[PDB]
Image 1 (cartoon, rainbow, N blue to C red):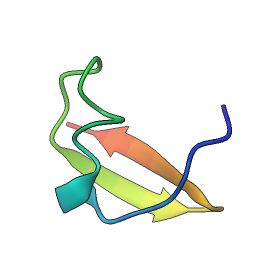
Image 2: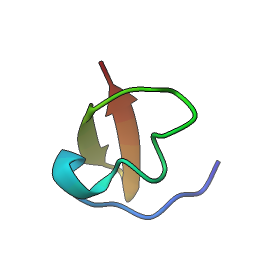
Image 3: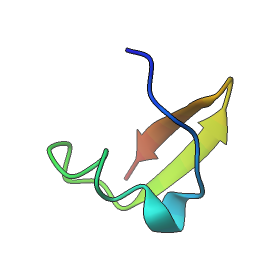
Image 4: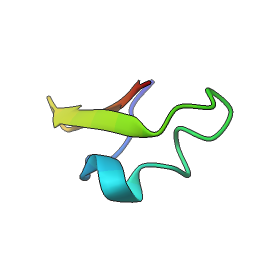
Length: 34
């Protein structure tokens, strides 16, 4: 899914359902990481 990009510190919103905390910004997309 096309999602904006941002640091893992401010990616909790898009990574709330996943229940993750960390993340990775790349390819104009933010990934959720445990």
